[PDB]
Length: 53
Length: 421
Length: 45
Length: 48
Image (cartoon, rainbow over all chains, first blue to last red; front, side, top):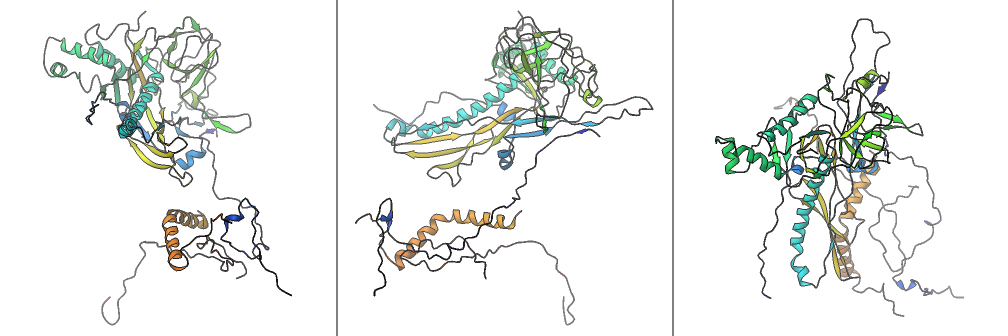
């Protein structure tokens, strides 16, 4: 034979997925969006009442 | 301090070589990974045999290649203070000058590579004004060496004179003591002619390099060295990697006084007829590309020897030289005196790869990037602006990413007049 | 080749292209329908 | 219905407390212009 042709390298962009994680608690937790940027690099929290007895 | 807006134009440049050079724009997405290199094959040459019974003498196939790559951007980064009236006044004309100087850089690079990687060398022991019709002798010598080596010239040919030798040729024409069409044109205008001695484009180029005389004396070859046309070779890991067909590393006695672009020839070694493999009467000429180590050089035509015995027949079918190196043969220089170079080439010998700079991406916020066509030459770059207040200024950058490549260094040539002493 | 990749590339290009006009339109809708004040960045105690 | 979808949501940070709505899905309409075959029949009543 001896075909001293021309050698290339082929990289195909069909990826091989490996990771698949499940997130069952963060979807269950309720999200709240405060309009208060004072929770910045500071210790200003928000105070909410507790059910009265 | 009265001042006007009429600008005194002072310089005007012409860039013919970058116009004649073909421009190549390969896909950037693939070039990002291929390491800014792309390979091209070389026209195949085949062996032949004689006789009836030729068992076990069947050959294989061997197709060589060359590689074309690119260097680094060429920029005009400058900074604009927003309060200086003399900076506010000159900004747009500075952009214009940036475009002009970028084009000038491109064509200067083309000229330098063509002069420093041209294998064909046409020397003369006297200047071009010495005898009559010796400018035509130069151009016809270039034509003849191309014809005899049987190089492809289908796209065209070009011969660039420097202004000195262009005027010498014009003087030769007007000293003819007659006036027809050629001498009358050379008198009324400086132009000798558009075609001379078979070249279909004879121009003058204001920025051809001056090739310094080499200091080399008495250099000989160390050991017999046979170079084999190969398309790939194994590396240390077993991977097959490609080989450029346009280089050969030669181990000499001492590479002192040898620099990039020097022209050499080995005693006894003769050219070949390429396709027909018939020896010529002219010594093979080579151009040293890189002086690696203190006893090695890299000459741009590979000296494949016809009489070589260690070559497979398909490899011998690529011979461009009658005999190999003989461990003692004298490599004699060809540029023995400083002289500006006239440069001839086939139009398909030099190309200009070009790439984009995607600075308009959404990654580069704050910057404003637009396209910027370089005039004269057919190239595109980026024009990027980013203001500043760490210095209360603004930064402007015109970038251009290209690379010249001599795909056929054996089709380029250099004319060296006055190579005496 | 991947259908998901092609569709998402088109949508990504479109979303990035129409970023500022959409932001201004949403701000105008909020201004005209909900409120004309912003307490978000007020560092005041 | 069990596999809840997710997509680029365009109502980011609805602000005061409960974000409420979630579950973004997209529908992608695409238009393909091409030459497809048509048949020339003969109407039994009149014409083609």
